[PDB]
Image (cartoon, grey):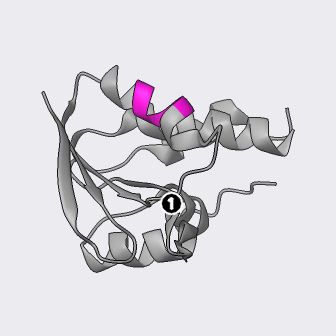
Amino acid sequence: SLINLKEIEPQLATDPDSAFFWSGRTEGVGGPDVAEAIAKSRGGVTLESTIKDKNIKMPQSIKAWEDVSASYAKQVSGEVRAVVGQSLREGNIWENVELPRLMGNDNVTKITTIDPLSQTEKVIFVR
């Protein structure tokens, strides 16, 4: 592996009701920077903003991101928000790594999606 997962994991923990996820684009609008803007404008964080703001060094590159994404998902609690576009990439981390671990996270109480362009919301899970 390209990273030292065991020492990074504690830094991926998030405050309750603060974690955001994201995937895809709608009419070409989306991606990690748009998700971070939506998240921070609403008082929350993303995986990328956590990595940047907690100064975690990230690049085998795909495996590193999968491991950190899974750890981030495992450590959230409360209400979760996800900026999910209409156009998703086959194999994306949100559907293949993160959302299954959110479903397996007994502390997740709600998942709400937000479109990256319109910001229309949909509740997709209530536990």
Asked where in the image residue 115 lies, by quadrant, the reply is: bottom left
Q: In which quarter of the image is the C terminus?
A: top left
Task: Give the amino acid type for the residue marked by disc 1 in the picture.
Answer: Thr
> In the shown orientation, is residue 123 left or right of residue 69?
left
Q: What element carries label 1?
A: helix
Residue 113: x and y in percent read 28, 54
Q: Nearer the viewer, residue 79 or 120?
A: 120
Q: Residue at x 82, y 54 (%)?
A: 59
Q: Is the magenta stretch mostly helix, strand or loop?
A: helix
Residue 75 appears in the figure: yes
Residue 7 visible to an observer of this rendering: no
Residue 99 vs 20, above or below: the answer is: above
User: Splitting the image into 4 quarters, where does residue 28 fall?
Assistant: bottom right
- Please say if 16 is above or below 25: above
10 Å neighbourhood of mark 1: few (<14), some, or many (≥20)? some
- At 53% from the left and 59% from the top, the residue drawn is 24
Q: What stretch is highlighted in magenta?
A: 96-100
Residue 127 shown left or right of residue 60 in the figure: left
Q: Which residue in the structure is indicated by mark 1? A: 50
Q: Is residue 94 left or right of residue 101?
A: right
Image coordinates for residue 35, horizontal then vertical, percent: 45, 69
Pick whichever, 84 or 18, lies toward us: 84
